[PDB]
Amino acid sequence: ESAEIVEVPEDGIVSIQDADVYVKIDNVPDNMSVYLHTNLLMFGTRKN
Amino acid sequence: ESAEIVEVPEDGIVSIQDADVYVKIDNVPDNMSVYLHTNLLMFGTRKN
Image 1: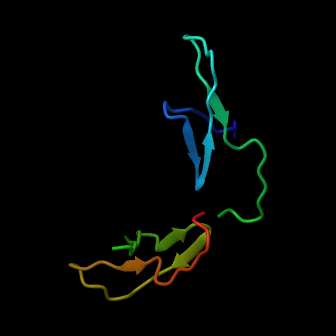
Image 2: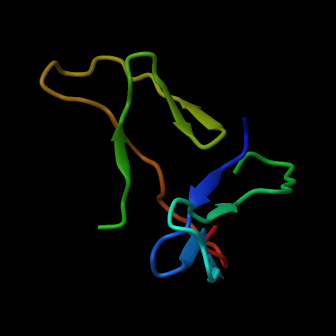
């Protein structure tokens, strides 16, 4: 339930707080979309 | 313009990301309210 999976915009740039990821996939079927997992592994000792 | 001044709730507890401030003022006039300055001095090297 804690996964945060967002949809990739048309310009291909997803922002994750200061970090920018450039994603371009060719030959994507017309009934499908591209998603990015934005917190696959995370670790921290304080909440903020 | 960068000041973030919020109004104190009825229970007197304001949360500032994990930190809690307890504010109780006596004899407040009925046409006035209590506000708290939540970022008087701040310093950081990265945006997040």
